Image (cartoon, rainbow, N blue to C red):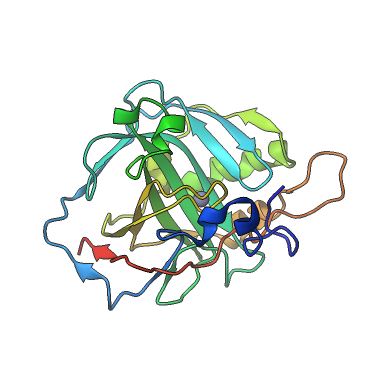
Length: 256
Ligand SMILES: [Zn+2]
């Protein structure tokens, strides 16, 4: 149904998902001069040592690297969060050119891509119940710029040929998401939403200030994926990002 084309893209989503014009939609532009340092924010705790990846899936709008979230293994806590959030999957948004691709922007600057590590609040028991709550998810967003290759990303890049089209999946065990993190965990945080339909307003966004560097060859491989299914007209999976939405009555806080 919805997608990123001219006839079914972000400006059309509100027809099927009225919440698209809601009060706490994502992504947003992060104005670095307006974001206020909050000394009460506790350091972020990213515990991915026991992460258990399972599979990688082309879902028609991105590719998701899925994790076993039936136990407290890979969790995010601390920072602005109260409680424990379990990693369920990560995916990226990217562009057709290096000058665009990220969903959040920083002083209107667009990065080549953006990584979203999606976590759900264990007090709600499962992801489906968590997305119906204002504090149901915590998404760790990390910007990607083109320059040096990210070694930890190569295993993901190399399996993309096996999931070129919509609906294809492939085994993807023993992938360590710690290899996708930048050095610093300094971050900005604000209350927002999922950036793809259903656009539910259930996300505490934690966006890292330090981008990771990936190579041109790495991002070029993302751009070879397809939005379409096998045996259908080829539609390159590029520009799968929603543009910045009105900040409205929200404050972005900085951990630094
Ligand atoms: Zn995303």
